[PDB]
Length: 149
Image (cartoon, rainbow, N blue to C red; front, side, top):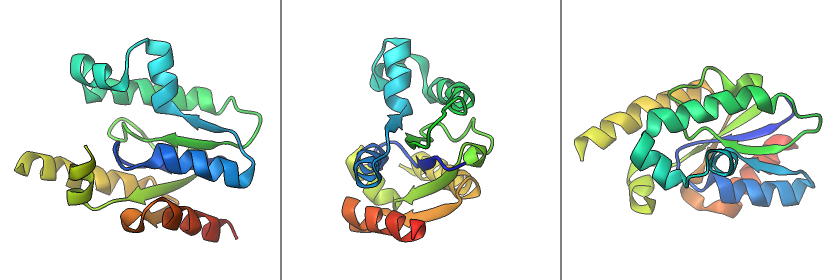
C-alpha cells in the first residue's frame, strides 16, 4: 500500500509508463504481463489466443496475492485482467491510465464497445487515482508525479 500500481487496458501503454515512473522515482518496476508470460512460458498473445482473456486475468489475479510478498515499494504495471480482480487497491495506490476507446482500438465493432464500457467501470472502481492518457506518456507521468507531491 505504497506500491504504485498502474492499471488499465492492454495496449494502453501502462508498461512503458511503469518503466519510466520507476526510473524517475528510483523504484523497481514489475510488469505482471512479463511475470505471467515468464512463468506460463507463452507470450501474452498466445495466452490470449489459446487460453482466452478470462484465463490471462486469472493468472493475474493469482499473482496479486504473491505481490503482497514484496518487502520494498514497487511500481507495478498490471490490471490487464480487471474482470477477475477484486480490489487491487489492497495491493497499493492504484492509478487508472484512462484512454478513450477509439484510441485504445487503434493501438491494438459494437461488441468491443460494450466490453470496453463494462471494464472501464471496473477500472475506476478499483482506482485510487485517474490519469488521463490522451496527452501521451510524459503527460501521464507528470500527472502521476503531481499526485505524489
